[PDB]
Image (cartoon, rainbow over all chains, first blue to last red; front, side, top):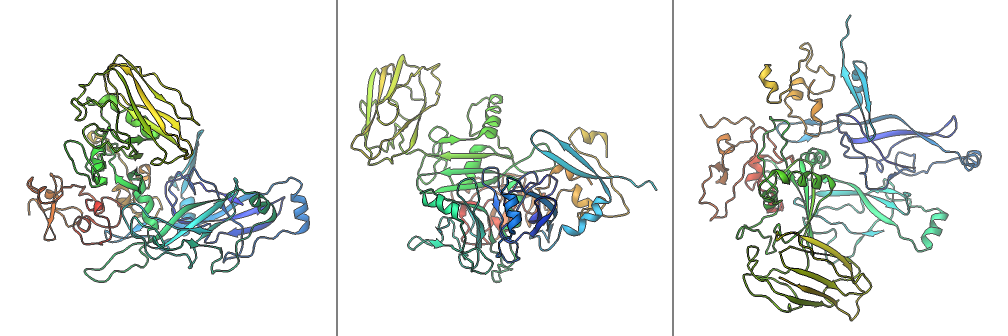
Length: 146
Length: 340
Length: 48
Length: 79
């Protein structure tokens, strides 16, 4: 598959890794966690990987170390050869944020974006504004009146 | 694949690992992160890995630890055997830098360059010089004005170039290792965001120069020096000695003191310019009676142009033409007309 | 906060003084008003 | 003292900073006079409200003097 990314929000992400899912027709062939080939280092908010002038990124493997190309049986191949399409889905994503040390090294080392999500999504509300060239999705706090 | 890197800018980088990407025709064959084989230990700025005197560098595998050579199916083999070409690109480059202790020993461990990229890019603007021997890309810090708290000194373009490369302010102009970088004598390419901002900032100033307009946050500017330069005081680097040279007040500008009728001629052979390209030709204005400049070079368009000066005011102009392919013929340009 | 600060373009915001991280993101309130953390964060997210 | 109240610990004097410039001598930032461009000395200012005014992790006093690396191009010494 050839694929690029997007990022609409308020924060960059260092060491971005999405783990995606393939579906053909009601079923799930495989769910990939991305290897070190298709990892991304920098991704600023309101941008994409790679930039707006290049071809997309490849993925072809499913093993942890990049080997073992993805299999399909006979019947799914013959059904796929009748013009049908597969669909690509995002299950979840992970990355890192930026903390700064003593007026020095901005250290981003295992400071994971995973363990701050369940807190923020049960605290804020969600606003999406859409226009003709890009969208935006923000989360904003509100008060429990109880 | 055989490939060698390069470097440009200011800083070195240790333990480089590029991630490359292959493309045939709209598709994507593979994107490979570099393994331990083709890793590069050092890159001194203005050089290449490996050095000038050796073979380039080959990559052939894709795994985590190097085995399992890169595959291609049958149809793309039939596409490639037809004689088409595949293309190779970079997506991102990570590495380390050099920090030390208080007069201790240099440590390079976890001092990753990857996290300092997006912090720098959204603050700076980009300036790329293209000379005919190397290139030079720089990032220069900027000032925001919508936030009053964001203190920094604001400076103009003509000082930003002065601090980007180390330039000597000779006689009001400036040079870079004895090449004239003037507002007048260089070719300045912008894009629509940059040009849209700067030409809509020019009408607010008295002096209609573009070096002394104010810097902003996000800009991408390319400068390029020409090959053949016709300064009339000195430095007309030219195999074609000019015909009917006028010698009256030829310092720079302010010296519009030759008003002659007739033609001047230049003939340039193919041994000193490189073929197969679309050159650009630029200049400034005057208030003569009338003139034309004729191009008579074949395998291109060989028409001439109308001069059509609106004023005396020193107005630039630019045309284009194509080259031959290493023939015995020379490109001949004539300047005909009455008035200057 | 005063009304004259809106003339020079300053903002105005409050927070909760029973946690140090009132919007849940791991930056503190003083880190987020005084923008001394990272520049590539957009300026409209500095308010807590 | 009175003209030595630096906000960020960039090890540099804010009196030396908002003014015309500051120059490195004997690994100490000193004030600027106009008889120094005959020697080869530069002139530069920055923002004192930040410890890293450019973004790369070298500090201001680090980058003004030559105290960080030698293979860095000499075109990148002002902050």
